[PDB]
Length: 462
RNA sequence: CAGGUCUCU
RNA sequence: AGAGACCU
Ligand SMILES: [Zn+2]
Image (cartoon, rainbow, N blue to C red):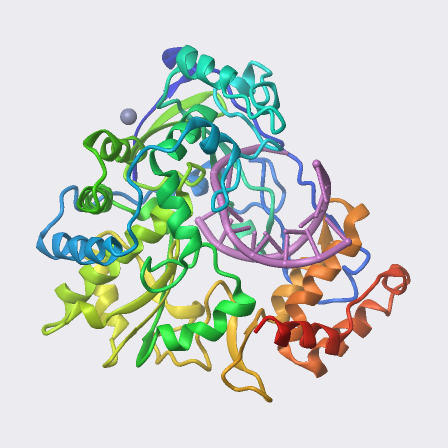
């Protein structure tokens, strides 16, 4: 992606959009019990912790664009992925505004706890003022779809969250692009059934993990991904995407049967307009992280990317022997012979993609099941039942989370969730974690799950 | 102060 | 109907 221009709002006639400037995060009662290196992200240009210009660092992620149109590898790549999707039988027909607004068995309803975006969020109009769970009213939606139209600008905000000390020094917080309610509704009408099918089918047919439950899914992955593993990381994935990948996505949607009216909506996320504070800017390429379909479209494009890199990097690649699952930019894949990712990374460079060794490794090493990660979790065979696989969130990560809160009223639920993650690391690690919690007065007031109870419930899942 | 998935009372 | 965990 690449910023095409920046203009003052006066010049463009867009309302200003300001976000909160102080973090909601505060040190928790456990802050000094556990070690950790993360602090709330820089939210303000005048943050004492900064070491660079804030706004400069914020938009450095739009590194630029290489290809605008598909070459032959990408075309073949897209067609291979699109054919594989055909067996899913995605319903290319348009979903109903009520279903799109209020949800289905495989698609959650539009979030009403959350901003309506441009221009409502500056006219003091909340989504609860337009929709109603209990009515399933679509009557006010239709009205505002007509008053304000589609292709409304995204509203740029900085993300309030823990970040490592380095990224706080270097001002590399993340940006969130608030969609307009109008475009969410309409994208959900055009692609709702695709979303539904994807959510229902995590695995190697969709090539996607959206909708997986790591407790159970992790036992399936070494069967779905047989042979030699490969993996790697992306830097600035969403923003590094050139328009060719949106052209490639259009190819897939077409091949599985979407109308041209449906396929036309892709250009409206490849080319977007954003308001940050008092300015308007234009972005070409780059996924707008905050549009409907963000996780799924990023995942689909990733499926195209991997295929294209393989056949352009190596000779004799049979794409039918590829197995992969993606969650946005996160990927785990296998092939019947080892794949050198150093060479894939070099081809990736020509495509404007920056690919690094899996898991912040210094160099591209071998990936096996003992050191692979996915959604940050390792893979650890159960000592009693080795075919049952524990997802393992690292204790270091869990320590970072517990050292802060945004609202100490819900401390019980926070610590419980971490316990659900911790116990997979084993009895010894879990009792060490629990007893550190107990070492402090509110720690003795919490209801903490029993290890063998967690385990027994896990086994019952099968 | 966005789009989502997962889990819990 | 609440809450938390995790991906962008
Ligand atoms: Zn533009």
